[PDB]
Amino acid sequence: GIREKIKLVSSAGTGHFYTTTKNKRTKPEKLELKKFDPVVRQHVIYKE
Amino acid sequence: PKIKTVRGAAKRFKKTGKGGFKHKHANLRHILTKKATKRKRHLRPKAMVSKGDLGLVIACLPYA
Amino acid sequence: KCIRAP
Amino acid sequence: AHKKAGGSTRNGRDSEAKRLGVKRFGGESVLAGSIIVRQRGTKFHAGANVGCGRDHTLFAKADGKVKFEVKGPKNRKFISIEAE
Amino acid sequence: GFEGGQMPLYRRLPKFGFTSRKAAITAEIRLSDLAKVEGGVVDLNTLKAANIIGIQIEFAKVILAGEVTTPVTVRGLRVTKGARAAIEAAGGKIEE
RNA sequence: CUUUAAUGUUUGAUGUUCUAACGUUGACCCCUAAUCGGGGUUGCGGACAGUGUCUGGUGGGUAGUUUGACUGGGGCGGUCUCCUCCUAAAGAGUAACGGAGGAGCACGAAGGUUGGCUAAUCCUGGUCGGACAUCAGGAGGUUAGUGCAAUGGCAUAAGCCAGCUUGACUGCGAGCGUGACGGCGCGAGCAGGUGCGAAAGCAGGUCAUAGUGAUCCGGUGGUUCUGAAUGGAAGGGCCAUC
RNA sequence: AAUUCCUUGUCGGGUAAGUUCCGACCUGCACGAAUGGCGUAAUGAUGGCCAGGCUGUCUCCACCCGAGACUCAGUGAAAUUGAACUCGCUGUGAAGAUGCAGUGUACCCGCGGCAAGACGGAAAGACCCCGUGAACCUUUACUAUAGCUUGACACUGAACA
RNA sequence: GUUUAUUAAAAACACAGCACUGUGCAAACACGAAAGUGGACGUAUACGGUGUGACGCCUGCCCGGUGCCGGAAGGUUAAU
RNA sequence: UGUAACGGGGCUAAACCAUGCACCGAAGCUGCGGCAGCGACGCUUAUGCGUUGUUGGGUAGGGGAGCGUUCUGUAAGCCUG
RNA sequence: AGGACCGAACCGACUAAUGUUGAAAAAUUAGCGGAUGACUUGUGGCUGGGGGUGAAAGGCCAAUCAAACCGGGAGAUAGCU
RNA sequence: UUUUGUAUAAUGGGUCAGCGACUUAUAUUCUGUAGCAAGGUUAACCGAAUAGGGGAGCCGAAGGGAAACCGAGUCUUAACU
RNA sequence: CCAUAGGUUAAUGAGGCGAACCGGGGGAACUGAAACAUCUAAGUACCCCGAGGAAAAGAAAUCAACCGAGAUUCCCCCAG
Ligand SMILES: [K+]
Ligand SMILES: [K+]
Ligand SMILES: [K+]
Ligand SMILES: [K+]
Ligand SMILES: [K+]
Ligand SMILES: [K+]
Ligand SMILES: [K+]
Ligand SMILES: [K+]
Ligand SMILES: [K+]
Ligand SMILES: [K+]
Ligand SMILES: [K+]
Ligand SMILES: [K+]
Ligand SMILES: [K+]
Ligand SMILES: [K+]
Ligand SMILES: [K+]
Ligand SMILES: [K+]
Ligand SMILES: [K+]
Ligand SMILES: [K+]
Ligand SMILES: [K+]
Ligand SMILES: [K+]
Ligand SMILES: [K+]
Ligand SMILES: [K+]
Ligand SMILES: [K+]
Ligand SMILES: [Mg+2]
Ligand SMILES: [Mg+2]
Ligand SMILES: [Mg+2]
Ligand SMILES: [Mg+2]
Ligand SMILES: [Mg+2]
Ligand SMILES: [Mg+2]
Ligand SMILES: [Mg+2]
Ligand SMILES: [Mg+2]
Ligand SMILES: [Mg+2]
Ligand SMILES: [Mg+2]
Ligand SMILES: [Mg+2]
Ligand SMILES: [Mg+2]
Ligand SMILES: [Mg+2]
Ligand SMILES: [Mg+2]
Ligand SMILES: [Mg+2]
Ligand SMILES: [Mg+2]
Ligand SMILES: [Mg+2]
Ligand SMILES: [Mg+2]
Ligand SMILES: [Mg+2]
Ligand SMILES: [Mg+2]
Ligand SMILES: [Mg+2]
Ligand SMILES: [Mg+2]
Ligand SMILES: [Mg+2]
Ligand SMILES: [Mg+2]
Ligand SMILES: [Mg+2]
Ligand SMILES: [Mg+2]
Ligand SMILES: [Mg+2]
Ligand SMILES: [Mg+2]
Ligand SMILES: [Mg+2]
Ligand SMILES: [Mg+2]
Ligand SMILES: [Mg+2]
Ligand SMILES: [Mg+2]
Ligand SMILES: [Mg+2]
Ligand SMILES: [Mg+2]
Ligand SMILES: [Mg+2]
Ligand SMILES: [Mg+2]
Ligand SMILES: [Mg+2]
Ligand SMILES: [Mg+2]
Ligand SMILES: [Mg+2]
Ligand SMILES: [Mg+2]
Ligand SMILES: [Mg+2]
Ligand SMILES: [Mg+2]
Ligand SMILES: [Mg+2]
Ligand SMILES: [Mg+2]
Ligand SMILES: [Mg+2]
Ligand SMILES: [Mg+2]
Ligand SMILES: [Mg+2]
Ligand SMILES: [Mg+2]
Ligand SMILES: [Mg+2]
Ligand SMILES: [Mg+2]
Ligand SMILES: [Mg+2]
Ligand SMILES: [Mg+2]
Ligand SMILES: [Mg+2]
Ligand SMILES: [Mg+2]
Ligand SMILES: [Mg+2]
Ligand SMILES: [Mg+2]
Ligand SMILES: [Mg+2]
């Protein structure tokens, strides 16, 4: 509906990304979460 | 004349050692964000064609 | 004429 | 021949039946993992060697015999696995 | 394949993979074949002459299948771990 | 560099003039005893017109076709997928254009965890203040609450509040459920790395059950897996995703 | 009203009596101005209505003359047809019976007549539905396309502003 | 006058008359891959198309829609 | 259309209720004779007999086993004025 | 004078009856309309099938017409009988 | 014949005789049978020709993986209890 | 004007028919896709031109893969 899809991209130099939705209207600030990067095999900041 | 293979069947099935057929699972092409990782993970490995379907597959692939 | 006409 | 105009119904809908209920009855011998009940709430509650999944499915955590019981101060129905 | 108009099984499932041209020009040789070459040496050429592999085969591999019970030099073929053991056990020489 | 002249140069447009292409269904001559044609000559027109290739518009003039199914005949009306209840005969399942309602989302917290807490309604007293605000006590005992239908659940709360957080993890998966099948569901445990907690532990989204769309074709990122003489590359595969 | 559903509208005329006709009213379901409006002499194998005359149209048929029909001689078709030793009734029954049950009636066989039935004969229902049938027709259905139309380049050149 | 030869002759079609509109002549338009031919050995008092339908009295308002005609500054826009 | 709402005749039981014992009644069961399928068991494997049990209604349809027709060989044989 | 009038030939076809395995695959009988015209008729010619021709009825184009006939693609296809 | 169901008043047949409908080719799979057997078998063609020659090929004795590749294992995954 | 066109005469050749096969110029639709337009049917049917006992093709600006082959045509494989 109103929620858009977004990529959360690894802060490690890998390509790795998670995908999710966001209400861009209500929450304009960028989502940052520590998530597991399986390429480096480490929890690291993801962004977007 | 020689039976013709259904070429679209040949691109989707491969004959295994005991003469079953492996195929790739449906539902992992797109609309992936909303699907759970567990669901997607279990769709990655190839699966065997079921007994009900073997007749249809064999008919399509006479030279498998 | 038509038998059992319209 | 006169035919009266019909009307319509605003009903007609229903959902697929979910195949809930008891899958293994008292005394039945199960392998670990075996679903014992599909349910909507905890109509039944997990007793010994029984897990409760996210949809309130109760399943065997050990191999053994299914055992239904009424226990505790609310007279709730529990399901356990008696290790055999 | 026709199922009455329902999307049939060979269409509701995805295509996968690609076909390797290299696979078509690669062969597997069994230990049972190594005695059939006539000569003792087992090159890619001697296998072709013994009608063991096709004329267009460029690569070949010797694979633990059957038995070898004779000294055989294997020259310029890949050989499996088990096949290597089997050939050397019979007094063979494997040379890349 | 912002504005702006002059010269040179490369172009494009426009307007005149010209004649030599081209036109002539103007005159005259000849082939010729011919209102065809051709040649000649002379006027007129003239790089226009016209034709070829390419190209935008228009185009029932013409053509090929499509224009769903259910249905107490067909049409008209209504419906078509998904969730909840009843019909449903105390396992599952079960039909009708049977009876009733909902969905096509929401949420970076409304998720995880630790710690704590407990409703509605009424009565009595109390500034503004009432039938109903906030305060105090009592009765009551969930008659509340649950992000949104209904059903089943829920106090050890699944309901309410706060702290810290990203397990809304990646790879897998004994074993089961449910499907003709495609598929869908539940899942302890194992490896890696994490959060909360002193710890036992709990966490692979949310009380659960709707919130969805196969394949094809293609897009984006990653990966040398492939790479049509060879090295590359294109394209393809595989993984992620639209 | 070649238009009015309601509707045989209402009022008047004509008739003993008029859902039609004529005149009028206007409540025009749903007239109307060149897909013309209103009128109009003449004309019409044109539609509607009324009179006189006329009559077997009719009350209600009668008789007669001819051609068939009928009989004899000659010639000699046809549609149809599972097989028939082919009755009524009331029931039954794939739901309307010569054929089933029960019962009634009925000696065998022609000829002239009549058409109630044999769901009689005739044409694989035109209606209706269905078929992922057809045709032809329509259009602001889709996709094309002749034609018409636009510009570029070619045939196509010169000189000067 | 004409018409459904063979179930409809009419109120249908035609009609003189009217109007709109196209057409400057190698006319418009039509038949025709074309040449050519009809239009016409005619030339706008002519020719084609369309609607209306002798005659009489007449023919009102609407250009928003769909066509057609005219415009062409600007926006958009093909090949190149 | 004709009795026409016991199938008819007719019935005062030849109706109805109760009790009882007889009998009729089917292609059911039994008897006698015969055929076939399947199983078991022993003869004994050319798979036959033998014994025993049991089964044999059938559309679509599956399975098994045959008859006859014309033509080729066997056949310049055999039958046949 | 006249798409003038009455009315034969001639051209039509309004009504009724008959006929309806006909005398006839459209007629006969009695009446009926036009009958110097937009008339009628002989002979010959031209127009060809998405084509002609049509005072327009989808009429007519050899007893055939919402796309003639003949041959061919051709054993079209037929989830129907 | 078609049907839930036909004496049906549902279909088809006037009768007889003759003819009239599951074929053929090539691929493929399964069953039976025969040969040979970890092998089996040749096509075209050659040929005094149903012989003999011809092993080009094809199927089989190895799989796993999209693939490189590895191989009685392999793929998956950083790695598998 | 020269000339050229044109005219006349002669010589030589062609013309037309015919089964299939063959090369070329044009070229459907039914149908299948369970509808249909891309696609299929199919470069088939059919029309047309031309030839010969055959035609066509043909002597590498061909393949191959670092080794090699050695014009064209036809058959069996490769391979559904
Ligand atoms: K279970
Ligand atoms: K000139
Ligand atoms: K020009
Ligand atoms: K059009
Ligand atoms: K119904
Ligand atoms: K009904
Ligand atoms: K929380
Ligand atoms: K009206
Ligand atoms: K008009
Ligand atoms: K007028
Ligand atoms: K009787
Ligand atoms: K009768
Ligand atoms: K008339
Ligand atoms: K307007
Ligand atoms: K306008
Ligand atoms: K035609
Ligand atoms: K056919
Ligand atoms: K029926
Ligand atoms: K019938
Ligand atoms: K076979
Ligand atoms: K065999
Ligand atoms: K087609
Ligand atoms: K079809
Ligand atoms: Mg993908
Ligand atoms: Mg009625
Ligand atoms: Mg070989
Ligand atoms: Mg059309
Ligand atoms: Mg078609
Ligand atoms: Mg329908
Ligand atoms: Mg139930
Ligand atoms: Mg029950
Ligand atoms: Mg808490
Ligand atoms: Mg929650
Ligand atoms: Mg919820
Ligand atoms: Mg390369
Ligand atoms: Mg290359
Ligand atoms: Mg009325
Ligand atoms: Mg009155
Ligand atoms: Mg009267
Ligand atoms: Mg009146
Ligand atoms: Mg009107
Ligand atoms: Mg007006
Ligand atoms: Mg008028
Ligand atoms: Mg006689
Ligand atoms: Mg009766
Ligand atoms: Mg008689
Ligand atoms: Mg009679
Ligand atoms: Mg009848
Ligand atoms: Mg019929
Ligand atoms: Mg109809
Ligand atoms: Mg007249
Ligand atoms: Mg007629
Ligand atoms: Mg008439
Ligand atoms: Mg008119
Ligand atoms: Mg304009
Ligand atoms: Mg009576
Ligand atoms: Mg018996
Ligand atoms: Mg016996
Ligand atoms: Mg029996
Ligand atoms: Mg039987
Ligand atoms: Mg006259
Ligand atoms: Mg006439
Ligand atoms: Mg007459
Ligand atoms: Mg007259
Ligand atoms: Mg007259
Ligand atoms: Mg009509
Ligand atoms: Mg005719
Ligand atoms: Mg047609
Ligand atoms: Mg064909
Ligand atoms: Mg046919
Ligand atoms: Mg029926
Ligand atoms: Mg019966
Ligand atoms: Mg019958
Ligand atoms: Mg009968
Ligand atoms: Mg029928
Ligand atoms: Mg019959
Ligand atoms: Mg017969
Ligand atoms: Mg010749
Ligand atoms: Mg089709
Ligand atoms: Mg040649």
Image (cartoon, coloured by chain):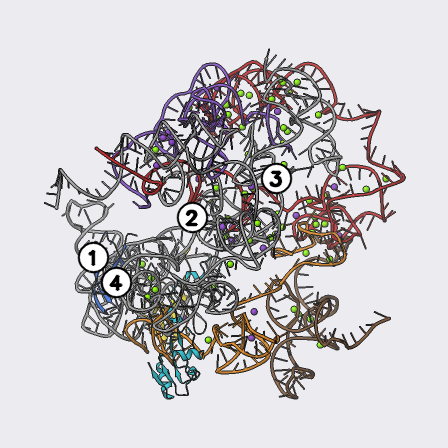
Chain colours: A blue, C green, D yellow, E cyan, G red, H purple, I brown, K orange
Give the amino acid at mark 3.
Ala
> Which secondary structure lies at badge 1?
loop
Pinpoint the chain carrying mark 2. D
Residue situated in front as seen by the camera: K70 or G120: K70
- Estimate the spatial distance between the alpha carbons at disc 3 and disc 2, rounded to whole Å: 39 Å
The residue to which callout 1 is attached is: A30
2 vs 4, front mark: 4
Q: Quadrant of ligand 47?
A: top right
- Estimate the spatial distance between the alpha carbons at disc 4 and disc 1, rounded to whole Å: 15 Å
Respond whether the residues carrying marks 2 and 4 are from the same subunit: no
1 vs 3, front mark: 1
- Estimate the spatial distance between the alpha carbons at disc 1 and disc 3, rounded to whole Å: 78 Å
Quarter holding residue K15: bottom right
Cβ atoms at labels 1 and 3 below 8 Å apart: no
Residue situated in front as seen by the camera: A8 or K53: K53
The residue to which callout 4 is attached is: A17
**Position above or below: K17 against I55:** above
The residue to which callout 2 is attached is: D10
Pinpoint the chain carrying mark 3. C
The residue to which callout 3 is attached is: C5
Pinpoint the chain carrying mark 4. A
What percent of the width, then of the height, locates residue I55?
A: 64, 73
Q: Residue at horizontal 40%, vertical 74%?
A: E57
- Estimate the spatial distance between the alpha carbons at disc 2 and disc 4, rounded to whole Å: 47 Å
